[PDB]
């Protein structure tokens, strides 16, 4: 929060770092760093202050840097400038001939002429404001990637783009005609920006283009033999809404995406059989008939407005993924969904009855939307289904033979609150999740013993008695309102994770928590005293919630515990032999402010974090002898001495505002550990 940081090869300065570099040469000469990342505030000379090991200088788009730069290392290969950086043409002419990748500053807006940009450059990106003409032999001859900024809107004529270019991206304002032989024969990716709305005729798109993306305003017809036979990816923009007739989409296309406004009829022999992915935009709402969709289609996504009926032999037998939008709510009868379909997702509005042999026997994943709320009877859900998710409004009874034996994942939605009796949930269910409103009794032999994960929503607040929870349960999450006593022989023997909710605040007696539990999480309200042999001897992680503020005496915290987190309100004395010797990570909450004497903190503790309000003196032989990471809070305001800190210490985390008081008696220039500062904002 007040430093620089090294990761892999990239050194990143602080986002607030604005200091001269004269003294960092040593730091920057570290032979394992390739790049420097500067931030928002840095605005200092970098001319002769950069060793030649760093080959990439990335400034970050909001950088405040605007210094004249004329002596970059002749080993630089990449540099990217930010929003406030300008250039003179001299500066660009002084760029090193090693440069391969360049983003110009966003202020720059002067005509670049011949023999200015580095000749060997391969990647060029113009700044936001650049909008000057470009003529022949201006762009480096071996350029491969060219990206224009927002404001560029100048004509591009023949032989200005290198015949080596593969990637071309226009910005928001570009809107000039593109004529024959302007786009290089090597181009593969072409992206137009917001305002491009110009006709595209034959022999304009090269024979090598694979990816074509239009932007917001493009809305011109696409005629026969305009799209090359190499195109595999075609994405239209918001406004494109022209009819696509026969033989205009090439026979190589695999991905087709429409934008918001496309809403034209699609007849036969328009969608090439090669297409695997089709996505419609928001407004498409035209009927699709029998032999229209390609026979290779695997993925089909409708937009929010689509709501036309789908009859037999419309969906191809290749389709595996089908996703409906908000508005779809048409009846689906028997032989409509192909027998290849594995993933079916409905949108908000779908709420039609689904009868016997509508859902194909290949379906593995069925997701309903907000409104679905019809009864589901026997032989409706197929026997291949593993994953079933209901939406907010489903709230119908689920009878015995409704859910298939193959189901492993059941998620019930916000409003579901019907009774669940025996032989409803299939043996084999692994994940069961109840939504907000579920609050019905769960008696025994209801939850399948195969279940491992069980979580309840806001409202569940029913008793859990004996042999109710399945034998294989490893994960139990209780919700906001759960506040019932948990008794002996309720939690099963393989439970490792138990999370209690906001309201839970009942006493826990001795043989309640199983000796398999490793993780215990108390909610906001828990504030009951914990006594001896209550917490099991397997527990490694203990987290207290907001309100827990009871004194912990000896032989309460188990001898297995490694990670202890107190909550905001915990503020009780901790004396000798209370924290187990196994502890390695200890975190106090906001309000803890008690004196800590010697022989209290386990010596094997490695991570210690005090909270906001802690402010007690630290004397000798108080801090653990193994401690490596010590963090104090905002209000800590005590002198630390070198004889008080253990020799193992690696990192001390401190509030900057109080450094002068905390480090009064510490030569920062002779310590073996690293000091990290934090701010209030």
Image (tube, helix red, strand yellow):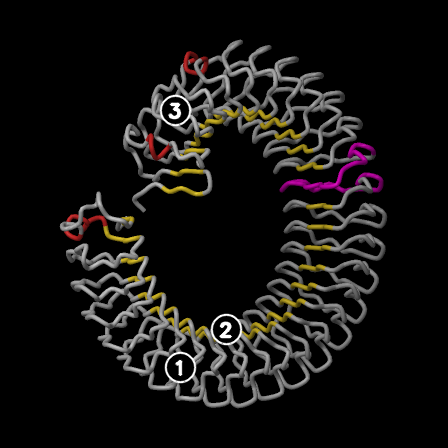
Q: Are marks 1 and 3 in contact (CB under 8 Å)?
A: no
**In-image side of 544 versus 423 (left or right):** left
- Give the image quarter of residue 563: bottom left
Q: Which mark is residue 85?
A: 3
Q: Residue at x 33, y 73 (%)?
A: 581
Give the x, y percent position of residue 582.
37, 72
**Helix, strand or loop at mark 3:** loop
Q: Give the mark toward the camera: 1 or 3.
A: 1
Which of the two discs, 1 and 2, labels the residue nearer the N terminus?
2
**In-image side of 336 versus 156 (left or right):** right
What whole-number distance in Å separates the C-alpha atoms at marks 1 and 2? 25 Å
**Helix, strand or loop at mark 1:** loop
Residue nearest the viewer, comparing 60 with 594: 594
What whole-number distance in Å separates the C-alpha atoms at marks 1 and 3? 61 Å
Q: Is residue 626 magenta?
A: no
Disc 2: CA contacts within 10 A as few (<14), some (14-19) or many (>=20): many
Q: Which mark is residue 535?
A: 1
What whole-number distance in Å separates the C-alpha atoms at marks 3 and 2? 53 Å
Q: Residue at x 70, y 54 (%)?
A: 307
Start-end of magenta stretch:
247-271
The residue singled out by tag 2 in the image is 457
Q: Which mark is residue 626?
A: none
Give the x, y percent position of residue 144.
61, 24
């Amino acid at each position: 929060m007040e430093k620089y940081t090294i990761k892999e090869t990239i050194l990143t300065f602080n986002n607030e770092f604005n200091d001269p570099l004269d003294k960092y040469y040593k730091i920057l000469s570290n032979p394992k760093i390739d790049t420097i990342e500067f931030g928002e505030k840095f605005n200092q000379e970098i001319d002769h202050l950069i060793p030649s090991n760093i080959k990439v200088i990335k400034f970050g788009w909001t950088s405040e840097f605007n210094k004249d730069v004329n002596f970059l290392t002749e080993s630089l290969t990449e540099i990217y400038y930010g929003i406030y950086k300008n250039h003179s043409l001299e500066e660009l002419q002084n760029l090193p001939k090693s440069l391969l990748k360049l983003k110009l500053g966003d202020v720059f807006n002067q005509e670049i002429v011949e023999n200015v940009l580095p000749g060997g450059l391969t990647h060029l990106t113009f700044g936001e404001e650049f909008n000057q003409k470009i003529v022949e032999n201006v762009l480096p001859g071996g350029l491969t990637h060219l990206t224009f900024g927002e404001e560029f809107n100048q004509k591009i004529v023949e032989n200005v783009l290198p015949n080596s270019l593969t990637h071309l991206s226009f910005g928001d304002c570009f809107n000039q005609k593109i004529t024959e032989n302007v786009l290089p024969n090597s181009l593969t990716y072409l992206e137009f920006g917001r305002n491009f709305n110009q006709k595209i005729t034959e022999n304009v798109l090269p024979n090598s283009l694979t990816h074509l993306t239009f932007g917001w305003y493009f809305n011109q017809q696409i005629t026969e033999n305009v799209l090359p036979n190499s195109l595999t990816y075609l994405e239209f923009g918001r406004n494109f809404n022209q009819q696509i007739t026969e033989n205009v989409l090439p026979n190589s296309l695999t991905y087709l995406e429409f934008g918001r406004n496309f809403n034209q009829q699609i007849t036969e022999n328009v969608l090439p059989n090669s297409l695997t992915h089709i996505t419609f935009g928001n407004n498409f709402n035209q009927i699709i008939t029998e032999n229209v969709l390609p026979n290779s289609l695997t993925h089909l996504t409708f937009g929010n407005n689509f709501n036309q009926i789908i009859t037999e032999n419309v969906l191809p037998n290749s389709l595996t993924h089908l996703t409906f939008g908000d508005d779809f709510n048409q009846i689906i009868t028997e032989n409509v969904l192909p027998n290849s379909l594995t993933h079916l997702t409905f949108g908000d509005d779908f709420n039609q009855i689904i009868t016997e042999n509508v859902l194909p026997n290949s379906l593995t994943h069925l997701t309903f939307g907000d409104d679905f709320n019809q009864i589901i009877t026997e032989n409706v859900l197929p026997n291949s289904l593993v994953h079933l998710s209901f939406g907010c409004e489903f709230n119908q009874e689920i009878a015995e033979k409704v859910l298939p034996n193959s189901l492993t994942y059941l998620e019930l939605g916000h409003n579901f609150n019907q009774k669940i009796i025996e032989n409803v949930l299939p043996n084999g269910l692994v994940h069961l999740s109840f939504g907000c409103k579920f609050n019905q009794e769960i008696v025994e032999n209801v939850l399948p013993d195969s279940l491992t994960h069980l979580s309840f929503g806001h409202c569940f607040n029913q008793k859990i008695t004996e042999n109710v929870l399945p034998n294989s349960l490893t994960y139990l999450e209780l919700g906001h309102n759960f506040n019932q006593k948990i008794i002996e022989n309720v939690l099963p023997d393989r439970l490792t994770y138990l999370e209690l909710g906001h309201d839970f605040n009942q006493k826990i007696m001795e043989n309640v928590l199983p000796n398999s539990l490793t993780h215990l999480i108390f909610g906001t309200s828990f504030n009951q005293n914990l006594t001896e042999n209550v917490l099991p001897n397997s527990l490694t992680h203990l987290t207290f919630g907001t309100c827990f503020n009871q004194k912990i005496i000896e032989n309460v915290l188990p001898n297995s515990l490694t990670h202890l987190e107190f909550g905001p309100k915990f503020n009780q004395k901790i004396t000798e032999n209370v924290l187990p010797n196994s502890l390695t990570h200890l975190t106090f909450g906001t309000s803890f402010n008690q004196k800590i004497t010697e022989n209290v903190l386990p010596n094997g503790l490695t991570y210690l974090t005090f909270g906001l309000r802690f402010n007690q003196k630290i004397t000798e032989n108080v801090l653990p002898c193994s401690l490596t990471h010590l963090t104090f809070g905002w209000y800590f305001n005590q002198e630390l001495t070198e004889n008080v800190l253990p020799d193992t210490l690696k990192v001390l985390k401190i509030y900057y505002g109080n450094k002068d008081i905390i480090l009064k008696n510490i030569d920062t220039s002779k310590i073996k550990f690293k000091i990290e500062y934090f701010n209030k904002n």
